[PDB]
Image 1 (cartoon, rainbow, N blue to C red):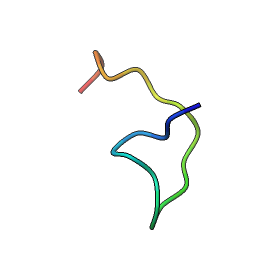
Image 2 (image 1 turned 120 degrees about the horizontal axis):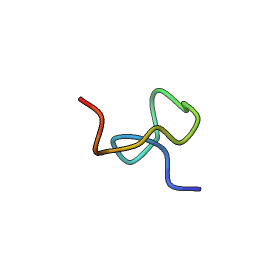
Image 3 (image 1 turned 60 degrees about the vertical axis):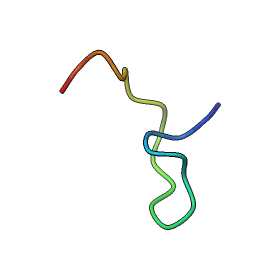
Length: 20
């Protein structure tokens, strides 16, 4: 769901916040 960093400019797939 929520993209890493909030999304917007840089719509990436959901990446574990726990990792890096």
